[PDB]
Image: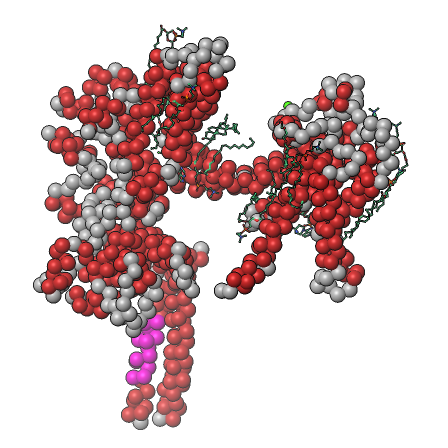
């Protein structure tokens, strides 16, 4: 495999081609395509970097290759089975891609690349206007390699858990210094991230140096409030921290416990940052609850100032998260941060607060007895509504637990699914409300109170209220005797039908909906919860040590983690990989050639043969004795 | 494409006729909701006339659907059209309206302070009950969706199935 | 007495008997070659 041959393999029409490769060559060159165009590997590299996304950089687009390519051993490649795997996948040649995948090294990595490349071509095929979409074909090819990567990880995990966790985090050096666990996140390949092995790793990254089988959360919270109790905690040895990726400054300190080291290990663990923010967030709500319930004067109280400080500094910390994320382009930094329910809510919560502060604070205190100054009122009322956002953000903290977190994810999924049942209920409501109002209140002029009256009491009927003494307004126990008139005897009949429909049909249908959909939503929600632990835990490695009142100093002073292996440990790891791939194919053949469906049929074939042979004996064996009848 | 062709393709697509009827049907209910909640005088309002026009012309369009169906014999044209829940309901809704219009409109306005004229009252009260039919027809439009439509069909099937449990409850 | 166990010991014997009939099929040819040659 040389460069000129590998050119020809992309530039050939004498075989099954991908019609959409050329449609991708255009977009990376932005318009230019002569009819006699011979594809070049510089142009293939730009397709790959486009498809793989992020900050991926192919070896075709580097200084070393661009020179030797223009110049033209050296035209060879060191790893040609990688160059052909990409070819077979860009050309939509799955049977060739599977074959070439089995040959070479780094099998689990190559499978996660292939999953990514097909997934990205499937998306462009949706977004493009062609005769055959081919996208369910490519989406099928992506999930085939994705299933292989998962099956190899389970194989490695059953052999050695610690070495399997190392496999998720070593750099690859032929795949743009990337990581198998990063490639799977890029493809949203969830059974791999929801797998026991990498959940075990995220839980060890959560600890840091802290050994949290001996310790308990009683003593971490204590040690945050009682700093000198940091010294009486059990930590981990460098040997126990070997499969865990670390920062530069971390490994230095682990390499050299000294007193100052034992503090550093504590305040830079993600678990400690969590509780150290959590406690500050709860102290925040207590005050903002005190401020909103207690009378507010012209000048803010000491409680209110502390609240303004937190939200101001909290907002600053959200800006840096945007402009320091894994995506390298702004528009990607934006869309991904707004892909989280509670980051959207914090954006509204922050913006709405300072509107309210502006009115509350920038209001001209014409003394009148406040709540005669209506600009002050609007400011305070925005606070009273904004605090709802900050209670609901507690569900973000609570979802860190294994039991609570999936239920928090179910609540969103079920609101989406119960939508149309609730639309029908809202129709039954108006079907009742409009006649009830029209019959009982005929002498009315137009007003926006009509819009409340057709909707108000019918809604409250769903929730256990009957308005017993308002039914039959002409009765003696009625509370609406001025409303008795012609045609009011109809409204009890109407309401009897209304509640029959809402409870006996529609509430119980909704109960029946949930009972019959609970399991598969719960199952999806557990996998989704596990996939998102990654984005959650990997953020705390980048967050500062101080929480959002005192973080301001960490910002001013300020103005990823990597897995390190010595060479013998890289050697032991590449051997672990090869061995576990061999075991995988072997056990696959054995299970196949040990099943009844496979033994019945190879028996079926031999018996068919042996039938022919005994006949091929039966004719001949007659023909033996004919001598001892004739020769004799 | 030619300009006039590109309009023809639009106004003769079934999706476009649907939303173009749907929006007119919603504008219809808004007015008939305004008419039924706001005080009614001797002479109909501009809102009420528009409502009478829609139901009159709506009725005409239902007649042609009957006499232009795939069945070629009248008695088959009839039975098949009445095989739909909401076409039966529209038949009652249309007939009941013009009874109410007759009383509301053909009533001798002996001035007395209306709601002393009891023929006017019956007319108005039929409107207030007839509008229920026209909210429930919105379930016919909503059943065009894949998620909502089956639930609309379940509601009918379950009323039929829960019948005897409800008879026992009525006995208790 | 189970099918998974009877299918497989059947699977093994049939593999053996295939070898034997062949170990007959070569030999049984080699019998009649007398009554073509000896005769
Ligand atoms: C927010 C970000 C940082 C996070 C930490 C924040 C904590 C900061 C801590 C303390 C700061 C408190 C302010 C001091 C005010 C003293 C004023 C005084 O004289 O005495 C006051 C005592 O104070 C009160 O009554 C105020 C209510 C206390 C609420 C405490 C909740 C949070 C505690 C944290 C728990 C966290 C535990 C972890 C979670 C489980 C008397 O009341 P008053 O206020 O004068 O009443 C108004 C009367 N007037 C206007 C007529 C005069
Ligand atoms: C990652 C994404 C999330 C984060 C995004 C960050 C978004 C930031 C959030 C929100 C910014 C936008 C909200 C609008 C601002 C207030 C407007 C207002 O009402 O002004 C008022 C006056 O103003 C004052 O009296 C001055 C006080 C306001 C300055 C402090 C808040 C805004 C500045 C930024 C601070 C936060 C910066 C945070 C740094 C990041 C006008 O009302 P008034 O004068 O009372 O009118 C009548 C007066 N009269 C009665 C005398 C006639
Ligand atoms: C001066 C006062 C100071 C002290 C007071 C303050 C004390 C602190 C406050 C509360 C006590 C909480 C203790 C729970 C910890 C148990 C251990 C555990 O398993 O943790 C899990 C919980 O992980 C979380 O993140 C839980 C959520 C945090 C608190 C949420 C506040 C809002 C809840 C209230 C809203 C309703 C309110 C209505 C009623 C008022 C995570 O672990 P796991 O995934 O199961 O796996 C084990 C992993 N690990 C152990 C290595 C982490
Ligand atoms: C008034 C007349 C009646 C109307 C009222 C209506 C009220 C409604 C109000 C509020 C409900 C709004 C929730 C919308 C969520 C939609 C997003 C979603 O589907 O899930 C996403 C977020 O996943 C999560 O985990 C989100 C968790 C948020 C919980 C918020 C609860 C707020 C409680 C407030 C308490 C305050 C109460 C007191 C206030 C004073 C996950 O996305 P997905 O997985 O792709 O989802 C597809 C799902 N599917 C494929 C299964 C279909
Ligand atoms: C269902 C089987 C048949 C059963 C038996 C027969 C029942 C069936 C038919 C007929 C019964 C209708 C007449 C009842 C009159 C008695 C009340 C009365 O005296 O006057 C009434 C006035 O009312 C009117 O002026 C007209 C009322 C009827 C018009 C609306 C028809 C609604 C039902 C049509 C569709 C139904 C179909 C539903 C099918 C499921 C009430 O007013 P008042 O009492 O005079 O109040 C005076 C107050 N003041 C002193 C302040 C001024
Ligand atoms: C139905 C079949 C066709 C379908 C379209 C129908 C639409 C036709 C459109 C417009 C026609 C409106 C009639 C004009 C009357 C003007 C009178 C006047 O001077 O001003 C009036 C303004 O008008 C009102 O207040 C009437 C209420 C408006 C209801 C609009 C709902 C439908 C809008 C369509 C939305 C569709 C959107 C799509 C759906 C999402 C003042 O009030 P009034 O009435 O004088 O009050 C009685 C007072 N008096 C008796 C004491 C004097
Ligand atoms: C596909 C199947 C579905 C479609 C089927 C179609 C079915 C059509 C639907 C219904 C038709 C049958 C309903 C009955 C008619 C009203 C009777 C009535 O009350 O008259 C009243 C008077 O009448 C008037 O004052 C004249 C106004 C009525 C004419 C307009 C409606 C009927 C004509 C057809 C228009 C729609 C045609 C639509 C074209 C298709 C009598 O009441 P009164 O005079 O007040 O009595 C006392 C008076 N006093 C106080 C002075 C003593
Ligand atoms: C297919 C069928 C089509 C034809 C239907 C034909 C039906 C047409 C029927 C009848 C026409 C009647 C007109 C004349 C009435 C004579 C009485 C009178 O004048 O005065 C009396 C009116 O008292 C009433 O109750 C009148 C209203 C009852 C009508 C009920 C209709 C039911 C429709 C059901 C819907 C069916 C829908 C079915 C759809 C499938 C007394 O009142 P007053 O003197 O005016 O008041 C002065 C009182 N003061 C002392 C307070 C001042
Ligand atoms: C000036 C003002 C103008 C604008 C305002 C008016 C805006 C319009 C009004 C409402 C917004 C509706 C938007 C839905 C469309 C989504 C696309 C879709 O999938 O369509 C589906 C919905 O098909 C239907 O037919 C839906 C029902 C129509 C509206 C029903 C009104 C009654 C509901 C209210 C009752 C409760 C009321 C209580 C609360 C008030 C059909 O498609 P599908 O089978 O899923 O497959 C896709 C096929 N397709 C896309 C090719 C079609
Ligand atoms: C008061 C004391 C208590 C009594 C009150 C009782 C009240 C009852 C009132 C109303 C309920 C009446 C519905 C009857 C439907 C029967 C037809 C049917 O079975 O389905 C058919 C139509 O299929 C559909 O999809 C029909 C959908 C119509 C929904 C109407 C809801 C009205 C809501 C109104 C809201 C207004 C509320 C406010 C008003 C002011 C399909 O036929 P099928 O598939 O062959 O069915 C066989 C089923 N099986 C084989 C499974 C067995
Ligand atoms: C499908 C859905 C059902 C039907 C429906 O929605 C769609 O159709 C809408 C039409 C609405 C009315 C249109 C115009 C006005 C005039 C306005 O006049 C100000 C007077 C005074 C205020 O103090 C200042 O002078 C008052 C409100 C009113 C009557 C609307 C009420 C709500 C109605 C009935 C709505 C109803 C819920
Ligand atoms: C219509 C306007 C003018 C009046 C007030 C509207 C009501 C419905 C508004 C005001 C405050 C709002 C709440 C503010 C905050 C949140 C938290 C969020 O996670 C879910 C929605 C939720 C719970 C909102 C629901 C709708 C809400 C209750
Ligand atoms: N952050 C959440 C919850 C969570 C999960 C795990 C831990 Cl360890 C802690 C908290 C809550 C928002 N969510 C989300 N928001 C919006 N749309 C979505 N689509 C998929 C997931 C989400 C993603 C998880
Ligand atoms: N028209 C409906 C609902 C519907 C279905 C599909 C679309 Cl795309 C739009 C609306 C509502 C009445 N129905 C019906 N009515 C009475 N008896 C029956 N037996 C079987 C069906 C029906 C037939 C479907
Ligand atoms: Ca109750």
Q: Is residue C21 left or right of residue A214?
A: right
Is the magenta region chiefly helix, strand or loop?
A: helix
- Does A487 appear above or below C24? above
Quadrant location of the C terminus of chain B?
top right
Name, please, the residue furthest toward the left: A73
Q: How many marks?
A: 0
Q: Is residue A305 visible?
A: yes
Does residue B163 appear left or right of residue A506 in this picture?
right
Q: Position of residue B139 (x, y in %)?
A: 64, 45
Location of residue A286 in the rendering, given as x and y in whole percent from the top left corner:
39, 17
For image coordinates 48% across by 12% down, the residue present is A370
Observer-nearest of A141 and A290 = A290
Res A576 visible: no
Return the residue nearer the eye: A12 or A399: A12
Give the residue at x 35% y 70%: C17
Give the percent coordinates (x, y) of residue A268: 22, 28
Residue in front for this viewpoint, B164 or B125? B125
Q: Choose top left, top right, bottom left or bottom right for residue A249.
A: top left
Q: Which residues are magenta?
A: C18-30
Instruction: Decide which of A336, A315 is in the foreground and name it.
Output: A315
Q: Determine if the magenta segment contains residue C25.
A: yes
Residue A230 lies, in percent from the top left, at 22, 19
Please report the residue visible at 33 percent of the width from the left and 48 percent of the height from the top: A187
For image coordinates 38% across by 31% down, the residue present is: A347
Colouring rule applied to residues:
secondary structure
Is A582 positioned to the left or the right of B154 in the image? left
Instruction: Determine if the magenta segment contains residue A546.
Output: no
- The quadrant where ligand 8 appears is top right
């Amino acid at each position: 495999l040389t460069i000129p041959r590998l050119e020809e393999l992309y530039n050939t029409k004498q075989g099954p081609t991908n019609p959409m490769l050329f449609h991708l060559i255009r977009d990376v060159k932005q318009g230019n395509l002569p009819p006699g165009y011979k594809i070049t590997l510089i142009d293939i590299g730009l397709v790959i970097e486009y498809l793989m996304g992020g900050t991926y950089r192919c070896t075709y687009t580097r200084k070393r290759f661009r020179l030797i390519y223009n110049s033209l051993e050296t035209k060879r490649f060191p790893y040609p089975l990688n160059e052909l795997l990409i070819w077979a996948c860009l050309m939509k040649r799955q049977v060739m891609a599977r074959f070439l995948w089995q040959h070479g090294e780094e099998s689990m990595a190559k499978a996660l690349v292939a999953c990514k490349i097909y997934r990205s071509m499937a998306y462009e095929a949706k977004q493009s206007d062609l005769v055959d979409d081919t996208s369910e074909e490519l989406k099928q090819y992506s999930n085939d390699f994705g299933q292989l990567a998962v099956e190899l990880l389970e194989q490695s995990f059953r052999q050695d858990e610690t070495m399997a966790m190392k496999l998720l985090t070593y750099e690859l050096k032929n795949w743009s210094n990337s990581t198998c666990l990063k490639l799977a996140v890029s493809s949203r390949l969830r059974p791999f991230v929801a797998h026991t092995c990498t959940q075990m790793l995220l839980s060890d990254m959560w600890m840091g140096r802290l050994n949290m089988r001996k310790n308990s959360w009683y003593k971490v919270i204590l040690s945050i409030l009682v700093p000198p109790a940091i010294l009486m905690l059990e930590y981990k040895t460098k040997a126990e921290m070997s499969h865990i990726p670390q920062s530069q400054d971390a490994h230095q300190m682990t390499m050299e416990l000294p007193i100052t080291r034992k503090f550093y290990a504590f305040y830079h663990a993600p678990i400690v940052k969590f509780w150290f923010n959590t406690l500050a967030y709860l102290g925040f709500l207590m005050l903002y609850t005190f401020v909103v319930l207690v009378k507010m004067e012209q000048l803010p109280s000491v409680q209110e100032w502390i609240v303004i400080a937190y939200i101001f500094t909290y907002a600053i910390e959200k800006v840096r998260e945007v402009f320091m994320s894994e995506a390298g382009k702004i528009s990607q930094k934006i869309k991904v941060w707004f892909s989280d329910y509670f980051n959207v809510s914090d954006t509204i919560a922050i913006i709405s607060f300072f509107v309210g502060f502006g009115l509350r604070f920038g209001a001209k205190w014409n003394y009148i007895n406040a709540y005669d100054n209506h600009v002050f009122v609007a400011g305070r009322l925005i606070y009273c509504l904004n605090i709802i956002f900050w209670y609901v953000r507690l569900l973000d903290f609570l979802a860190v637990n294994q039991q609570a977190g999936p239920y928090v994810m179910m609540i969103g999924k079920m609101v989406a699914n119960m939508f149309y049942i609730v639309v029908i209920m809202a129709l039954v409501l108006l079907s009742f409300g409009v006649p009830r109002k029209a019959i009982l209140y005929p002498h009315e002029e137009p007003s926006w109170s009509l819009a409340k009256d057709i909707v108000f009491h019918p809604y409250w009927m769903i929730f256990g209220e009957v308005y017993a003494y308002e039914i039959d307004v002409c009765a003696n126990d009625s509370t609406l005797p001025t409303i008795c008139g012609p045609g009011t005897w109809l409204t009890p009949f109407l309401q009897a039908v209304y509640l029959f429909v809402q409870y006996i049909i529609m509430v119980n249908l909704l109960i029946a909906f949930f009972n019959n959909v609970y399991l598969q939503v719960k199952a999806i929600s557990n996998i989704v919860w596990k996939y998102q632990r990654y984005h959650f835990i990997m953020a705390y490695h980048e967050k500062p040590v101080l929480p959002p009142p005192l973080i301001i100093l960490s910002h001013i002073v300020s103005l990823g983690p990597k897995l390190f292996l010595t060479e013998e440990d890289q050697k032991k790891l590449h051997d672990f990989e090869e061995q576990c791939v061999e075991m995988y194919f072997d056990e696959k053949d054995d299970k196949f050639n040990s099943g009844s469906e496979e033994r019945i049929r190879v028996t079926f074939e031999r018996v068919e043969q042996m039938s022919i042979q005994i006949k091929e004996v039966g004719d001949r064996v007659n023909y033996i004795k004919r001598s001892l009848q004739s020769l004799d």
